[PDB]
Amino acid sequence: PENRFLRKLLKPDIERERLKAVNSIISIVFGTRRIAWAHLDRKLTVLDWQQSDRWSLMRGIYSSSVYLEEISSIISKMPKADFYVLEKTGLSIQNSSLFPILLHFHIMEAMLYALLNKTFAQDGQHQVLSMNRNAVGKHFELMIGDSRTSGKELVKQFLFDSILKADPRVFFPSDKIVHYRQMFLSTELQRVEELYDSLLQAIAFYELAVFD
Amino acid sequence: LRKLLKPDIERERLKAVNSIISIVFGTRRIAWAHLDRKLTVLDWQQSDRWSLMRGIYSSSVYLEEISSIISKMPKADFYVLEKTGLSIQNSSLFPILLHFHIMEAMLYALLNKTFAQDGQHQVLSMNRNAVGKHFELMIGDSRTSGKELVKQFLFDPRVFFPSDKIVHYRQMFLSTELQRVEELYDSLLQAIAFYELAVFD
Amino acid sequence: QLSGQQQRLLAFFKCCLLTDQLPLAHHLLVVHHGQRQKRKLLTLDMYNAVMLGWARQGAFKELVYVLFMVKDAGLTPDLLSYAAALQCMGRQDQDAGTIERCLEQMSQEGLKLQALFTAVLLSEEDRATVLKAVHKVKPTFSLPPQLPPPVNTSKLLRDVYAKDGRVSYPKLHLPLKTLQCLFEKQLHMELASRVCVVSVEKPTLPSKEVKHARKTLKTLRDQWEKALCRALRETKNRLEREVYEGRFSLYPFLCLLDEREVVRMLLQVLQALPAQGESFTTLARELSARTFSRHVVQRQRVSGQVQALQNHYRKYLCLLASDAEVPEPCLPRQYWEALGAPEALREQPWPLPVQMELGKLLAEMLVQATQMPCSSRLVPVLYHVYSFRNVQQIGILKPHPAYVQLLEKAAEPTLTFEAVDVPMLCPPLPWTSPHSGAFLLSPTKLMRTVEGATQHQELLETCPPTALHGALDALTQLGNCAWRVNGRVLDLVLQLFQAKGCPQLGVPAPPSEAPQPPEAHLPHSAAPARKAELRRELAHCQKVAREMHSLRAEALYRLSLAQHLRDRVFWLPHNMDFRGRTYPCPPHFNHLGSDVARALLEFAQGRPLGPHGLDWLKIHLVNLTGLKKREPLRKRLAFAEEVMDDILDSADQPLTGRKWWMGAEEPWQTLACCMEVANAVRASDPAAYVSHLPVHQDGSCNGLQHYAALGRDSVGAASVNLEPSDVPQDVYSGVAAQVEVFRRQDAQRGMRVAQVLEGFITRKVVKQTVMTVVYGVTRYGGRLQIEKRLRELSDFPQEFVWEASHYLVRQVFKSLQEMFSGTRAIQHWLTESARLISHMGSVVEWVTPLGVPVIQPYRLDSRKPNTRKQKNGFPPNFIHSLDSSHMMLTALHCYRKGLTFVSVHDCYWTHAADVSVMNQVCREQFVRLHSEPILQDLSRFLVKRFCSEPQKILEASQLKETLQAVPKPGAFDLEQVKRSTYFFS
DNA sequence: ATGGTGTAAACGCCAGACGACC
RNA sequence: GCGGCGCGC
DNA sequence: GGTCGTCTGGCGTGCGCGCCGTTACACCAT
Ligand SMILES: Nc1ncnc2c1ncn2[C@@H]1O[C@H](COP(=O)(O)CP(=O)(O)OP(=O)(O)O)[C@@H](O)[C@H]1O
């Protein structure tokens, strides 16, 4: 039932032998006010983690000429990778009140698919895929009822404390750890919930699919 | 020209245009038309049905369909996309609005090839009411089918059909009249309206 | 140059002054000094605060060090520092030479000895010590003597404050020693904020499972209490470490209340949390507000104000006591100020940044502190969940489902109320200022502001103090009314509530009585119509169940207090809004409510009926039934005697037998009146019977009654019963008849719309439209209202509703102009004036005849005014200020004759014997109010306040031309109102 | 029963907006 | 303060 | 920068109190 589990986990269907030889991934989590990403490798090391806070979007109008010029600026800093992982949400068209959020999510996902998937005309093979949120939550046991709880305690165990336990789950660079700790201390006052989810989703992708 | 075109384009580059392509799409098919500076058509084609708009919304299917359609289209300096009229307050028009926004985002992202380098816009948005008032097919928000105007122009006409290609457009025009197709007429009407208003004052 | 950190440190130092840990603040101060960049944020106010704190405990050396620090700095020593120096010099009893040198140095800077006593506020002990010190220096210095209190000399309020007139003030019935213990009971209830009330639900049988659940709850709550105490101790231990090293911390704030009331408050907050979660910021704000309120209440025990309040209230009760007497009778406020009054000190809230951190520190302590067994290892109760709320992404705290199941299994029979939402058990404090009011140990606002409105209080504080005495006396008079709960009606209501309730009488029904759709074994997906209707039926049933649950949720909370306050005497204080209308403070159980809430209440004090009480009781009963509203009083009285057998049958056996009272518009009040009438008739001497029920008098269409008075319209006043008449006049019937005759004449000549509308014009169609003219009703809303009534009507063809609705709105608006013309003229004039003054960039401001200043809050998002809302709101807000003033004049004149007066606005309530006196006073004060010129003084005030500037005279000219175009009045005489019979009848 | 699964594309009016001129 | 309801003048 | 007439889109009875809720639904296995 591993194949059915991967069909439920990953909506795009990609062959297993290509997934076995992946070298790097980038996980992207976006919200109404923020977007963040992280970088990882086969021996899990974390070279980059960042967030883009201020933009002039949402408000009352939706115009493609603003979305394009903002997204094209955000993607400029993203380095190359073999695959890009996007988070998918359980929101649907049935929620009549939450429909502007669905508009924002669908427009941003469509533009990310259109820009980030280069060489599609020449080759025809995908490089951007969607991973489910609740399935990631169930692998870290963060699910009370049908609702997913925060994961800040888990990243507090990953960083600011070093218990190897003969099998650590994530690695950090020696020189860049101070900036990471300072950023995590800065973000404790106002809780941004996407910075943690990006890293958790990257670890989940490496564990469930690549190394299985 | 805020009322006619939503993105602000300077007047100097707007008038000096060699050719333009007008794209009008819907819930079943997409069609385009190619016209150069002189009012002579160069390419007018229609697309068959697509796999989209059935059930679930997926981005990979949109990417494949648009990448299939864009390849056949020839190169032109400016692209004009229609700006339709829909209200976010209306609850029964949500799926059509979502499909229109996804298609518009896909087209804006894929067509502006040089925007990553130069930073200029090659895709423009034109409202339907301005064309409906200028060409007076139907005054107001209502829209006449426009078949009679096309029969008036083809089969002193404003638009000229070039030699050795008139037979192809005549063969297409006699067909599909029983079918309910409107994008072919609206694309050419939008192209002529753009050339009348934005160019030559 | 406002900065967040400066304000944070100022709040820190003020909190350290309120608490006892002064040396910690002295440490942070010395450490902030010694930094070139930390020195610049220091302010003179912080130095003066620390100096005053050191001075209050007589530490001479520390004041010298602070003065040395200020001298090293460039700040100029204010007079408050001099007052703090003299306080310490006095209390330490130092030599006269040093204090004389200090006064000489103060004189060198030009400061006045009277200025330190007058310019800066100080405590009584501080001023006494400074006076002792200066008396030791100069024994000839004496404070200026006080003055007798001023009296109002306005034309309308001259007779109230006259000493020569004869007065007969009312007195209470309870003895003095009875009244003294209720003060102690209310003090006990106010000291502990929460109040526990037993619920009125049917008691469930306790099984073994519920007892097991309750035992588990008790053990878990004990463990949670221990864990919360230990967590609070550890948190306080480290935050205080932060203060050392010069960091700011909420440690001064966390030692404000002792550990016990923090743990109990946190446990109550955890108990009040819903099943689905609630936003984190709301919890933070509620926790900060609650802890500030608890500090405000609990400081007064330590400071010693409770004893002084006890003594002064004990002396004050002699005026209201039955056995005790006073030398010279006077008003309650004048007696309260004649005796030495407690000084009240206003308090300033902490900044938002200091308030927001405290909610998080204590809302994040709770999640970590509490743990629960799995039911092994312990699993936490409270979780952080990221979710969607109100078309926005927010954070939510969510509880464990096992906690919810355990709390649903055990049925707690108790409810919780705040102390402010329950009626008082003692007579309230009199209204003497906008700052001091009804409640014993809680602050109250004179005007109700929804959010962030400070312009109302600023205008209330810059007026001369003499202007507000009429309003304050009216509020105090309304406060002192005594109430008690009727019991038979309560027993009947509870008997219907516990079983399935009757919903036509106003009693909600249990959720188990909701309708259930039929269940079919056939799958709905087989047929399109079946699955189409099934979803609609299920959604409709869920919606009606959700609607049904909330009504019972309201009724339970309403009915618990009635059972709680049985066999007790209680009082209800009042406040105001920005226009001038008066409302009670307790929301759940008071008058101004529904039928059931009004039926429960009655007067504690009783009066003998007299020669004419029974007739007024019968007329009130006939009015409550509502069958006869178009008839004189004689015919109502004749109708009352014809139905006496049904009255006795309903009084003796309410729910068994003939049920005549249920057919009335107000059945519960009808039954409450029938019981008293049946009691009174069977007595031997009806004129000697004691009564406790109010009698209601009201007048229809008050706003039109004021518009006709302003314009002196001869034809307008007849419809609104201002002129004397034998039969009351109804405006709605006149509008209906004018519309009908217009339709009759128009139908003959070329119409088809009028032909089908024949016979369908009545009072019901036009009643809502005529009622809503005082508020501005446009044509659009009028057509909507007429369309609704036309759709409810069945015989009318539904296709032609649109053109018929337009025709009716056009003809009613044409008919209104013929009767009312001056009303339209004045309305247009006020609209134009508001539009122009809004275009100039100002909000509308005027002054009531009694002296209350009124301002309008409407403003777009140092913000630009909104023209449309000001222009539409000015005319309905003027008339309501005039309606309130007749009421506050009528109450003050009814007090002097010895009457009990309570009023729901536009309606007057009193005993049966006093109706004639109340009517005469009402009519006399109406004639006196409208005899003065209102419109001309309004124009003069507008021309003085606005358009008085030497700049932009061009825009000033049009305003001067518009404002002086006051309409001319009519030929109607105002003295005829006193002989009217149905003015407020 | 619960857990867990699968399914769900009808009219009028007035305070601004502003391009340009000043 | 987003939505569904109820009450008083 | 201020202003200066001129065409267009939003809006259409005042004030004051309460209670509840925030993907839903039908089925199937165990
Ligand atoms: N001054 C007022 N302004 C607005 N609505 C009012 C009002 N007085 C009463 N109402 C409303 O009108 C309804 C009361 O129905 P009615 O009792 O017929 C009013 P009425 O003015 O007393 O007519 P009535 O004298 O024939 O009874 C309630 O919905 C109540 O909220």
Image (cartoon, coloured by chain):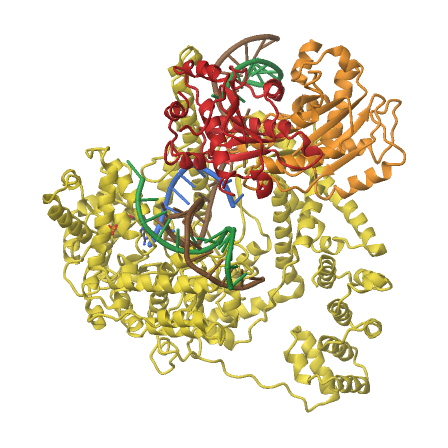
Chain colours: A orange, B red, C yellow, D green, E blue, F brown
Against A114, is C737 above or below?
below
Residue located farthest toward the bottom when viewing the structure as drawn: C140
User: How far across and down, in percent of the image, does residue B42 sit?
Assistant: 53, 22
**Viewer-closest of C242 and C430:** C242
- Residue C561 visible in image: yes
Residue at 75% from the left image edge and 16% from the top image edge: A209
- Residue C895 visible in image: no
User: How far across and down, in percent of the image, does residue C960 sit?
Assistant: 39, 72
Against C688, is C504 above or below?
above
Residue at 73% from the left image edge and 37% from the top image edge: A51
Choose top left, top right, bottom left or bottom right for residue C984.
Answer: bottom left
Q: Is residue C451 left or right of residue C156?
A: right
Q: Is residue A167 left or right of residue C909?
A: right
User: How far across and down, in percent of the image, does residue C313 sit?
Assistant: 53, 68
User: How far across and down, in percent of the image, does residue C729 sit?
Assistant: 18, 57
Q: How many discs appear?
A: 0
Residue at 40% from the left image edge and 80% from the top image edge: C153
Residue at 53% from the left image edge and 67% from the top image edge: C458
Quadrant housing the C terminus of chain C: bottom left
Choose top left, top right, bottom left or bottom right for residue C881.
Answer: bottom left
Quadrant housing the N terminus of chain C: bottom right
